Image (cartoon, rainbow, N blue to C red; front, side, top):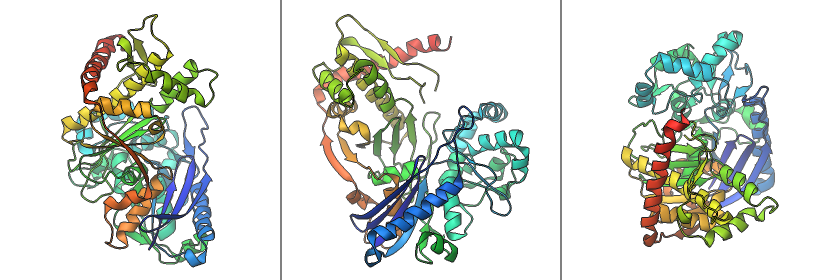
Length: 488
């Protein structure tokens, strides 16, 4: 029994064909262009998503061949919240504004001055930020009133592709929630909330939950994509959440730790409870929420430091530095690092190394950074705990998992077992799974992990709890001490 996931990614459009329960029959990809017409702008062409999607779906069929082509449902995921504008005829008004876009600081300031940023965050479980569809909408109204006045539909990237597939008009709950349109209490688009963006409430399509069938592939879209006519299409899926699912975050208390360029932490919870510190999403798993967080400098901060410390080491840099840090005690001999090189995610704090002496070596520096990143991950976990999400079962994925030293450090700091895994194909897998569970009940959400490369489960050394606890206390006190100085 066969199923497809499609991922409308930021620099890449990826589709996979899975034969259940545990086989990836085919993978297709295509590059996507991130434009920036002015500094801090991040835009994409929704017509390239669609062209990418047609190519990659058709290639799936061409790769697997007709004799192994029997797809039974498709789910589309991608980045969010992207802002796509359609006029009354369904045509794209201007290029899509991506979530990394930075053009709307002024409107964020107004929004923040015009509503209670806490009441708001308690309401939508997301903060008043440039990532709100609402902030980008206010910017457009003031900078491109003609675009603004022509808006019949505002939606996200994968919502747009789904419309092209089914002719339905909806958005993912999660696009609307991250976007600022949904009240957690009601789980629906609120007039109230749309009004803030000064668009008519008709301009935002009804929200739709990922796990439910959204519609079927139309005749036009069968033609353009190769997909069978009438193929069931599921709700669109938020990319980072589908990634959490694929990593096996399916039960309340499950936590994913993503050692990417920027770090993420994603947790499944029965508790919906916004917090100034952590953003909220619905899980794909019905009934669950997915509080999540991001840290700006993670693998990026290591790449920076590896270049400084192993200038002409090439790729071996990390391997070489990992080895040095290995020979260095936990806590790095009194080194304490704050890892906020782009800021953190509150203020504009900055990277700090302290406790340095002429005895420290490149290994201590590398280690201190390794430990600091771990420590920031710990802090999130403590926050999750505080809010009542009860973090307990831990997974790590992405690039940093290739470092046995880093992961040993992570576990010793967290003082819980950490299950390492590889999930290279990414979010597309979380998406195939949604359609997998919709086309029968021979499978649980649970079962996704047959599709990923689960690896070593690392146990902490309990004798390290006492040093990392004190380091944690130091890290915390370093930041509290340097706060006033950072906001001088």
